[PDB]
Image (cartoon, rainbow, N blue to C red; front, side, top):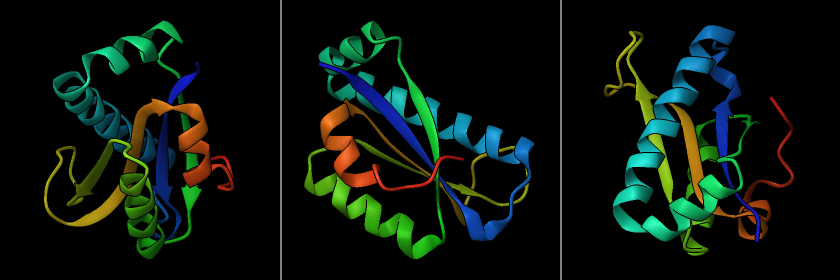
Amino acid sequence: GEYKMILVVRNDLKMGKGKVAAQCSHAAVSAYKQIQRRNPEMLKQWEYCGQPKVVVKAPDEETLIALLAHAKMLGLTVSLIQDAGRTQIAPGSQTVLGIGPGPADLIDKVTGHLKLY
């Protein structure tokens, strides 16, 4: 089946395009490391599909946590990235929630309604 990764960006932070790109990259690398360490097979299946990544929007932090819980309840991998205002991942505000890599059908149940970034 199809496998993918969704990157959810927090809209109320009003991050610029470059910052979003960086935060999404942090989430993708984090998720890759996680999935590699927990389900090598699903990782391979995601790579076979061309390791697709799609960026969507969430209005605020409350939404990110709700998505996190839902994804967890479906057995999906989750990656939460915090930024402090620099180039490094560090305690601060939650910027992006990475969901997956995981089965596309499950992922869509969690984020399918979110608007594309």
